[PDB]
Image (spheres, coloured by chain):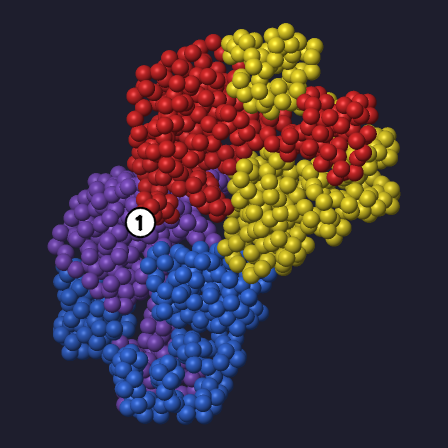
Chain colours: A red, B yellow, C purple, D blue
Amino acid sequence: KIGSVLKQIRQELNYHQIDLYSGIMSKSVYIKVEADSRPISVEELSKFSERLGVNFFEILNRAGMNSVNETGKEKLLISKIFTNPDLFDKNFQRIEPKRLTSLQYFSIYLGYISIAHHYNIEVPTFNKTITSDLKHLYDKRTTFFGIDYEIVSNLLNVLPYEEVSSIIKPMYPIVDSFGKDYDLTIQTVLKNALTISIMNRNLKEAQYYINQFEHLKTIKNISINGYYDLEINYLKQIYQFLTDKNIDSYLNAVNIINIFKIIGKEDIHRSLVEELTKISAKEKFTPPKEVTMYYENYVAI
Amino acid sequence: KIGSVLKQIRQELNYHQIDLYSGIMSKSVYIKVEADSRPISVEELSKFSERLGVNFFEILNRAGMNSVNETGKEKLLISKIFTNPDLFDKNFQRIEPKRLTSLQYFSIYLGYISIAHHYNIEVPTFNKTITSDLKHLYDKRTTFFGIDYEIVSNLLNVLPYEEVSSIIKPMYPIVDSFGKDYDLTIQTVLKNALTISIMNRNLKEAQYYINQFEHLKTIKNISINGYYDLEINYLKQIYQFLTDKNIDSYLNAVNIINIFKIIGKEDIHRSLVEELTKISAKEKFTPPKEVTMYYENYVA
Amino acid sequence: MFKIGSVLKQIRQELNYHQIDLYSGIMSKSVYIKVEADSRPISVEELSKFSERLGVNFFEILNRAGMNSVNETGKEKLLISKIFTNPDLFDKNFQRIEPKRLTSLQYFSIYLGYISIAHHYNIEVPTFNKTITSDLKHLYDKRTTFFGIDYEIVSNLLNVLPYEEVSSIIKPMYPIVDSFGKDYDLTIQTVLKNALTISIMNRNLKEAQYYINQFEHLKTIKNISINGYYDLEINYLKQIYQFLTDKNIDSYLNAVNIINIFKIIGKEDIHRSLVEELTKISAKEKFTPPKEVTMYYENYVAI
Amino acid sequence: FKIGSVLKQIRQELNYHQIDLYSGIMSKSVYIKVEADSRPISVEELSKFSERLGVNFFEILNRAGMNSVNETGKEKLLISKIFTNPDLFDKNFQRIEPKRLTSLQYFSIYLGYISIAHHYNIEVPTFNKTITSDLKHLYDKRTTFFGIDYEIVSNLLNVLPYEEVSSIIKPMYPIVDSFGKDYDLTIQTVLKNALTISIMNRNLKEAQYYINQFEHLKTIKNISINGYYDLEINYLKQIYQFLTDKNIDSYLNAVNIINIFKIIGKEDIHRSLVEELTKISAKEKFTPPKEVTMYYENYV
């Protein structure tokens, strides 16, 4: 872990053991730290971190913090259980019971309920406990962490918008950034939410999400996800088309879909194309020959 | 610090001290942790976070890690001096002599050299020691850390490419992801180097960086910056225009440039609009009316 | 009236021919001289022959002689343009025309010119509505074949009459089966374009396609000379028709693109006309025209 | 030349009596004669009946059959049969070639055969031998030109190197008056064809010349401009701006205009503009859009 990494970085930058502990601990003590035979304090690592000049978060990662613990494992097992709907059964029975052990397990658990509805496996349990679970986790909350946003994102995918919208309102506006991981999670929710909104032609909720996202940009140090910014901006375009049948807005939307293709985002392109097709279909309006030609051969697969 | 946040998160989620300290430490000690009268260890805070179910890094950020030490305070000061150049001279006379204390300081140092070149200020010692400093910092180096990528990105901003490329080559390709923070840095060097390359019409170097970025996209657990991906693709489109004058590649570029305006990234758009006007000139080509419409209004 | 002889002499000498070359086998030297002196009538037959000898097109010679005017009817038709700029002349003039509005199909066309002006400079011509309907019946109930002038008359009517009243008169004049010259082609085409503009305007999709078809039919006629500008504008009205029929985003795009070509090639007045059209067409459909075309229209109205 | 019956046809159609036509122009027995086609009618007389019937003088003539009438007409018509039946070339060329200077019409027809001949790569050695003396003989003492002169020039441009015609063209422009729709078309064709050639050979100085001559036409009273030509000549104008300073906007306008030609159905012009855009591009070591190279390739 840490200790090794410190000795490594220390020597790389050509610092003697002395430059690191000089005014932080004993040589007898510091040797124990590099030997990985004495836990280092968060505050201590921090000082060494500065002395060396290498970022604290980097040192941690360079020492193994990354899917490196009980819950970490349980989470990886879903990308696999996805591509093997039979490796399900034995796993859904060990998790289901402990789905409220911590917020992280509720996420994972919802991850299975997703894989379920997908391949169409059975989950009669989900229908008779989702409401009980939610109340137990979001009835008396005053603060939300990354994991809560991750959870709401999973919920949106396995639950009718009506059942999840109540949970969301209390989680925005965001006023601070608590890391890049946190920044990403709080943004995913807005994207998912907005997409669904635009899809139910629920313009009032759409505007709300579009606005929450515009707000995030003003937050000091927040790391906006470019792909998201580009997709939400596409949704903002459709939003204007639904509001005043603006033609430029429709063009801007088609245009952004093409950009996603031009930069190699096959997945997002397919999604945004099928998305645009349906929307127009409802508006009783035909999309360009371009987009439709893509839809077909995305059905021929 | 940490303890406060730990307790705060614990109660928010309705847990008892038992649920946390059990199997890790005595209830007697866990009280000192939540009181911050005892320093917690990286090993412990990790178990506690796993228990709480909240991101380890998020807890640390909430606990204040985000600026604190003198190195960070000095970093913030840069942009201050940037807005008010009058702060330069005095602060520079404090940093300059410490530029080799640490990689963080050398970066900050290169920061002033940037502010200076912008306000035509004179920094005579730079030219007198830049080559020596770089030779002293990167000759016995074998592996590189995030900070080095930040440094290289800076060098490209205050030094002629030729004096940097050699420091840049042994730093790629990237093999592992070491956190979103580190991910973003190794990406920036490519964008800045690729940009300078396309500008100098150095096609060989340009395609090298283009491939290095593409390689990152294959690394497990790497956060690709969407904005960069969209800008590098534009440099890639320009790359093709310069290679074999393709009218469509020129269109595509113009197209991405316009997307940067629609989604509201005004500064990248200003940037790219000048970049195209200058590239088109060297190629004896007239950019679209639209592009120069923006360039001209921007310059004012 | 026409100076055909002088024109002949002008061409004959420019091409370095001698009189014998022209008259031999057609007339005596004595008479050929009277012909060039413009002191002896020349037949269509003879002129056609001198035309073959000279090698210059018969129509051009007549044109060079002045077939573009020299007669009472032409002067009246010319006088209209004046009255438009200076309307005080309307009255005393409209008192001469009106009573002769049926003398020939030409005078009737002129007559409608006046009725058009009057409408513009808000003048009141009560006699018009008092007789127009009786007039048109008198002019078209016993008809079987239609000439170029009848198509001009129809375009005039579309300008000073509700569509429904002019519509019945048009129908029996189509489809066209044969061309009778560039002059005739242009007229049978203008009716279609003007009628189609009005169709699409009243969102009358079935009438609209009628004309669109009539037009496209003209393209299959031997030696028909399709007016390129019309072909473009009518294809714009075709793109609109398709949008109004099933809201095609591409169809709307085409319409906008064609509107742009008119700007690129410099056809100012038509570009103004179309930008104004699309702006109204669109509103009715609860759509907003592109920012582009709205900037133009708003700027044109700014005069 | 059955003008008398056509007057009868029209006179009755418009429900007019014989007295409505001859009252003030001629006697009754003479007019009777006229409609019977038993007495030639003078241009003046015909212009008068025309005003009484209210129907176009030129329309009445076309309705009477001026659409053919004489030997020169037959010879012109025969050029289509031969263009699609080369085996018919030799018999008629032996007849035409010798009459090529009989009149300007015949010289035009003659040029028609030389075009056909070049197309089917047929031998016509008498041409290369007498073409120059011919031009000299027909255009040395010329001061003013007529329609057939512009027709002849279009012909010359099609079977002769540009450099041998340019000099005969210059004296025929600018045009000052219009002399009917037939004439107006002819004069525009020369410009359109000549500008096409100039743009190809990349002769910019001359290209501008034809572009300006066309522009002047628009300022002429009663001139009937050809929409298709206007659109196509403007296309060449855009290509002109492109060759002059590689203006990207100009290039895109060219492509857009090529598209319009397809959108409205002019399959032949489109096929033509598609080819030259490809050849013109290739020369400039420039590649056209995927769009137009597609159409071109599939046009073989």
Q: Residue at x 40, y 57 (%)?
A: D259
* Frontmost residue, A164 versus A280: A164
User: Of the residues shown, which amino acid type is indicated by label 1?
Assistant: Lys
Which quarter shows the N terminus of chain B? top right
Q: Residue B30 appears at what percent x and percent y? A: 62, 10
Which quarter shows the C terminus of chain B? top right
Q: Is residue D149 left or right of residue D12?
A: right
Q: Residue C5 appears at what percent x and percent y? A: 36, 78
Q: Is residue C22 above or below residue A205?
A: below
Chain for disc number 1? C
Instruction: Examine the rendering and report whether any part of residue C36 can be seen.
Output: no
Instruction: Examine the rendering and report whether any part of residue D117 can be seen.
Output: yes
- Using the rendered view, name the quadrant where residue B103 is placed: top right
Q: Residue at x 56, y 9 (%)?
A: B17
Q: Which residue is mark 1?
A: C238
* Frontmost residue, C142 versus A37: A37
Q: Is residue D271 above or below residue D107?
A: above
> How many numbered circles does the render carry?
1
Q: Residue at x 55, y 71 (%)?
A: D203
Q: Is residue D100 left or right of residue C195?
A: right
Q: Residue B11 appears at what percent x and percent y? A: 54, 9
Crowd rating for badge 1 (residues with CA inside 10 Å; few <14, some 14–19, many 20+): many
Q: Secondary structure at mark 1?
A: helix
Q: Is residue A221 left or right of residue D141?
A: right
Q: Is residue D251 above or below residue A272?
A: below
Q: Residue C282 appears at what percent x and percent y? A: 36, 38
Q: Residue at x 40, y 51 (%)?
A: C258
- Using the rendered view, name the quadrant where residue B297 is placed: top right
